[PDB]
Amino acid sequence: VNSFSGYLKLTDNVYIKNADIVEEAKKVKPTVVVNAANVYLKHGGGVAGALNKATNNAMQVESDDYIATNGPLKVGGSCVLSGHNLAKHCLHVVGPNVNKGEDIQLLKSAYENFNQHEVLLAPLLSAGIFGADPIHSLRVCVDTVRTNVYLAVFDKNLYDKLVSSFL
Ligand SMILES: OC[C@@H]1COCCN1c1ncnc2[nH]ccc12
Ligand SMILES: [Cl-]
């Protein structure tokens, strides 16, 4: 039993809700929140910009030190950093950005990072400003993640379509 509330169950391990991931994290304080990161951990917009803003830019400061030490992530890769005031940890995961021409097959690799954590709060990878089809992203999530994932979808209209079209 966990403290996630109001989710629709899609499969044994995948749950979904129309919610602002920032507000969800602040309420639940999960062990792991997933950020929709880029390889430079530049948290300018989308989910990343919103999460970073909620940390008063502490996420960005920590991220800049991480990059200075380690260099950029790989598309499809991840790193674990602090969750600041939002969660114990933040798993920064880089899905392919279609508006950069990146290979959508890397979306499965991106979701595989979730399997290293027993329970996560997460957005749909490569959705929003990363330009992929969110219906496809949900399909890949369900077919790749085996640990317990709670998906927050900000847009109510998109949430209803993902549910109604879910196979
Ligand atoms: O689940 C990811 C969805 C779908 O594509 C990107 C937008 N999404 C968000 N969902 C929930 N909270 C959010 N805060 C900022 C963005 C955002
Ligand atoms: Cl977005």
Image (cartoon, rainbow, N blue to C red):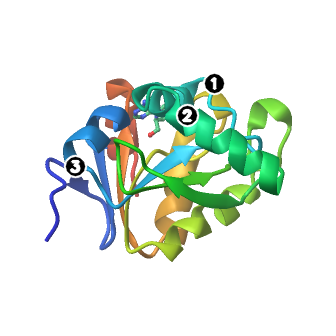
- Cβ atoms at labels 1 and 3 below 8 Å apart: no
Instruction: Name the residue carrying label 1.
Output: 44
User: 6 or 9, which lies in front?
Assistant: 6
Of the numbered discs in the image, which one, if any, rests on residue 48? Answer: 2
**Quarter of the image holding residue 32?**
bottom left
Beta carbon at label 1 within 8 Å of ligand 2 = no
User: 55 or 167, which lies in front?
Assistant: 55
Q: How much space separates mark 1 and mark 3, taking CA atoms?
A: 24 Å
Q: In what element is the residue under mark 1? A: loop
Q: Is residue 127 visible?
A: no
| Residue 102 spot, x, y in % from top left | 83, 44
Q: Residue at x 65, y 59 (%)?
A: 78
Q: Residue at x 15, y 58 (%)?
A: 3
Instruction: Name the residue carrying label 3.
Output: 28
User: Which label's residue is closer to the chain start, 3 or 2?
Assistant: 3
Q: How much space separates mark 2 and mark 1, taking CA atoms?
A: 7 Å
Q: How much space separates mark 3 and mark 2, taking CA atoms?
A: 18 Å
